[PDB]
Length: 362
Ligand SMILES: Nc1nc2c(c(=O)[nH]1)N[C@@H](CNc1ccc(C(=O)N[C@@H](CCC(=O)O)C(=O)O)cc1)CN2
Image (cartoon, rainbow, N blue to C red; front, side, top):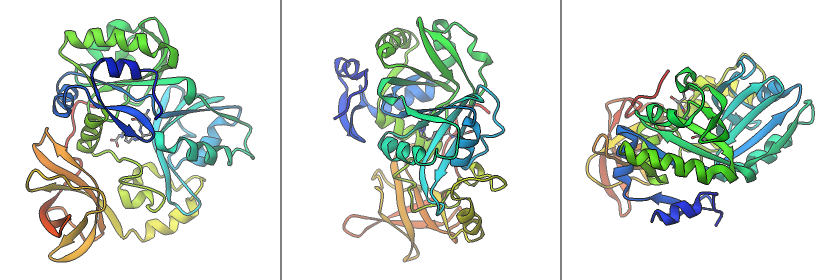
C-alpha cells in the first residue's frame, strides 16, 4: 500500500490500519465513537495526505478551471476557495473537489485519493486551448484537517497570523509551527475547522506540535472511520459511494454548485438533464443497530424505489443512518424498507437533510 509521510506517527500511536484507496491509513486510534466525539466536542486532527493536489499556473488559470468545474470560478477573488464537481461530456460526475484561487495566474485543485490519476489525466487532456501548465504536486504535499468547535482557539498559538480573519472557504499562506503552510477554513466534518496544506517533509513536526496541543484540551487524532461518520452526519457526499460518472449533480442534491449561465464541460448535457430530474439522494434513519451498505435495495410498500449509497452509525444522533439514491416520488416522512442480506427487511424513515450541523461557519 501507499503510505503518507505521517504513516510512522500513526503506527507509533497504535492505530488499526485499513486499506483505503490503495493507502495504508488509520481506521481509528482509540475508537471511532471517541474520535467522532472529539470532533463534535473539541477537536479531531485528521491526516488526509492521501488526497491529491494539482497546480494550475498560467495567464488563463481562471478560465481553464472555470471550463472544467461546474461552479463559477471566474468570479472568485484571491484567497477564496470553492467546492464544486467536475463533469464529463454527458454530465456524469468525474469527481467532486475544492479549488483555491491563489491569484489570476495560479490555482490549486484538491481531489479524492482514488481519483488522482483519472482526474489528472482528465484535466491535462483538456489544457490544450488554454495558456496554462498543469502539474500534480501530490507526491510531495501533505494535508492535515484540524476540525472541531475548539479548533481555532487551539490551533492559533502555533500560527503566525490571525485565524479569525480567515473566513469560511477562504485561505492564506502562513507559518504553522515554523513551516510554510497554506491555511484554509475548510473541512469535511460539519464543525468549524481548518485544513493545513504543507510540504510532505514538514508534516511530521507540524503533526507532533499539534498533538501536544490536543492532549492539553482533550482532543484526539482521528481516523477514516470517524472521518466517514462525521461527513455522513454533516451529509457531505463521498465520491464513488454517493456519486460517480453515472449520476449528474442534480440527482445527488448538488444543483447549487452548477451554474448553467457559463460555459463548461457537460454543460449542454446538464441543460437537458435538469429538465428531467428523476432521481434524488435522501437521508434515511433506520430502526436498529444494523448498518446499511452500498447497494442494498430500498423499497416503498413493497415496490423498489432505489438503493443505499452510504451507511453508518451516528453516535451524535444515536441512530443507524444512511444516504440513498431513490425515485423522485420519495418524500420526507416516508416509511421505507432496506433489504439486508437474506431478504431481511429493515424499516427506515426519510428525514430532512442534513442529519446534523455543528459549528461550521457561513
Ligand atoms: N480541501 C479539501 N478538498 C477535498 C476534500 C476535503 O475534505 N478537503 N474531499 C473531496 C470533496 N468532498 C467534499 C464534500 C463537501 C464539502 C463541504 O465543505 N461542503 C459544504 C460547502 C459549503 C460552501 O462551499 O459554502 C456544504 O455545506 O455542502 C467539502 C469537501 C475532494 N476534495
